[PDB]
Length: 125
Length: 123
Length: 120
Length: 121
Image 1: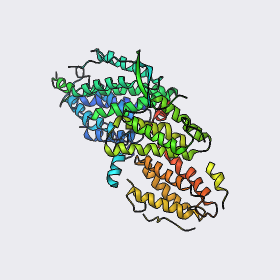
Image 2 (image 1 turned 30 degrees about the vertical axis):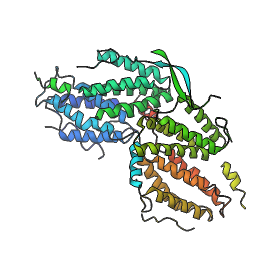
Image 3 (image 1 turned 180 degrees about the vertical axis):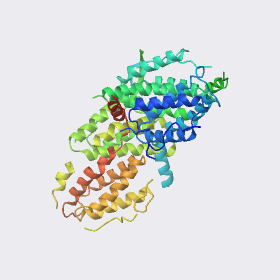
Image 4 (image 1 turned 30 degrees about the horizontal axis):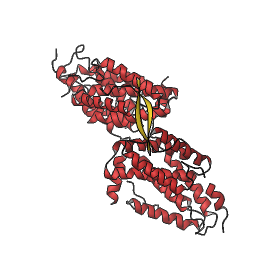
């Protein structure tokens, strides 16, 4: 399985992905990745890991809404099952990755701190 | 503390793909949610009874293995808020809708799939 | 979209700085504390009541009484610890929390200092 | 001027973990330095670094409590001696070094969305 992304472009304003800063260009690249790997049965494990690292930078820079948009972008592209070939069940494989590697990052960071106040108090007593 | 009468704007009525407001076509559900957000930002936010109805519908989508539809509606609401940010408008309604998005809607996304079963028929 | 009539609980009346005909800050603090504690169980306070309270906090700011806003801020914050500790009222917590973090705390960013200068 | 804190060591402060002990230490610090004209600037810097750890661990409400604790202790001007105007000096520190940390981190992201869009066009 070939690599679609270059690991050396990202360090390991909005964070860069694969040397791109414009969000529409990032989205366009992600669209290509999904579309070209469905026919191989899904993406390379390392490209997923590299993309997750970018998504986590988004989460930690108060840009969860950009993770949300990219997630739905990938999700909607998987509606193309009647148009694109898939070997090794690429559509199922991408949907697993979406549900297991990507979507769970939407709740990595909380935006309410009731559990934090509780944890500190439980540790205080 | 005392009781007061007031008139308030409501977008929804108190009374397989679950329906929302007696709508079956998801594109019609989407256009209805879009105008709900766009028209209530200027009010300072939506009516809590309308949010509760909408959240109940999202939970049904989750329970029906349609998380991808919740994801789409989540992003639909989010991009309506980008109109506020860009034009530097409606800060009160933005903040209320933002809290709904981040605390009431998005947590459902992490609370087999319906497409997967169709995907397995590979032709 | 349509108009509906309802009954809603209001904690304040629409008619140094006074709040709700109160001059003693201890009685103002007592009142705010009751307001948070009672409305937490409702899912949050009435936006008209928040507006009245915020304009009062503005008057404190505009009169160099930032330290009173800071005190009321923490008072509200510690009411929310009761929710956290007893894991209750999650809706009213989140609404009050947003008010604290977005409507109140931003106001914070020497009426005593003038009196401090008289050292005896 | 003497150092009240030890540079060599929820986030911990000065090897303390329970929040009431941290509050107790801060209360002592304020109270014992008022008579010196205010704290040592390096102790302020070390305390600021602890407050920033609180802010970045979603504990601004603990920054809020400590801020109000220091603020309220400055009401003690009729009871404690001060040289170099220690009460004024602490109040400046409160208003300039401590309280502005309460708004270091935003909890609404309208400006983030605007920034990204303005960068996009």
